[PDB]
Length: 350
Image (cartoon, rainbow, N blue to C red; front, side, top):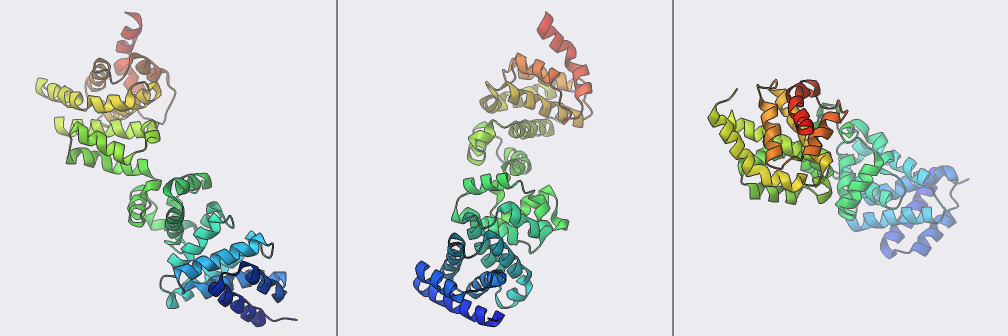
């Protein structure tokens, strides 16, 4: 016959003493002596969170530890934590009035609960989709990275299968805006190829020295992504965009400049492409799309094929594999094949 207010008052005492002593044994004892009904469990947990919110970072850590302990002891469940967490989230506007940093603080609780296996990233994404509470979801990610590491967070985020763009407010739901927001939260590391796509051409223009470009890639892209087909697409596309922006049937002078520019970038291209037929195919697709965007100017695609072959950027087998590859992810394959088919036949038959 115990009321809601009695049990909340009892909860408050347990919290005050745990924050003082860090008594795992006595906190559990306190909660057990409460003999709280199962229906009060979520209310108890949300009280634990709210009592701690406007206290120190250290007291917040202690409150999260208490929650985890109650689950470990079978006093409450992951489901009870989720109920409780959602109940606090719903009060976010009210709490923010008196606790201006409440979102950042709530993000601390979410991060620690995920770490202790009380809630998943994929679950957390559900009530937060489309920028609910926003930037709360991103602040949870911030805290995860800080408490663990970027490699851990990157793979957990990958495992969650959450679509990051879908987590943004609707008016922000665009790849370019997404990158702006993530960079501002210190979360750019989650989308390195998107960041590459937006920055690489700018970087080449800034300092086109082959050594600088290579070192920039080494610094900003993982060795594993160096062998990723998407990376190669962006790499090649960026070089080609640079070349054509500087060089523009063309004059003898334009053709020579174009060749000299390629000759300067060749060692960088070779460093990533050598001994990777699949990547060399992806590089040909990048070339295909590049020429496609200029309506396949007379002889352009073919002259680049010839350069790629002669400069040992692309080996014979990749040219033939490109022709055979069935992808329709890239426009202009039929028009592309029309231009280069005789040259390819020549490689095979002459």
